[PDB]
Length: 85
Image 1: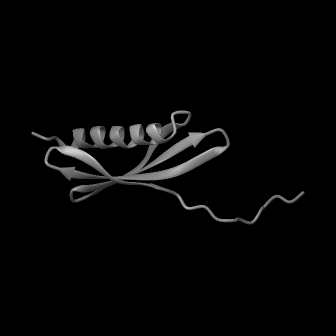
Image 2: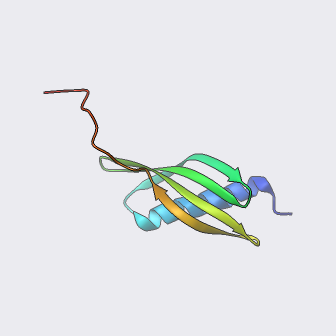
Image 3: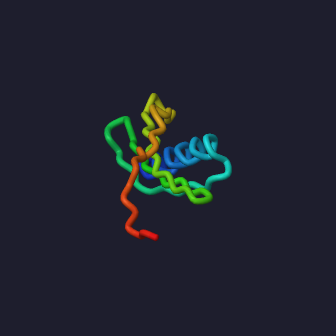
């Protein structure tokens, strides 16, 4: 029986390893998970030297196997410095 509880264990592991394939110097941790039918959107948080990029590895159920639809990264823009020197 494909136990739903075990499905999180698989998907979040696939998700983190993909981010570790994109950036082996970074240490990734799970941030948020959403079961949406076949497609699980797992938000993760990838931490690096002076970087912290929130990703979303959107995985899909094809048969028994979990395939990555996309790896999304948080979009950046110019901010307003709270601290001024």
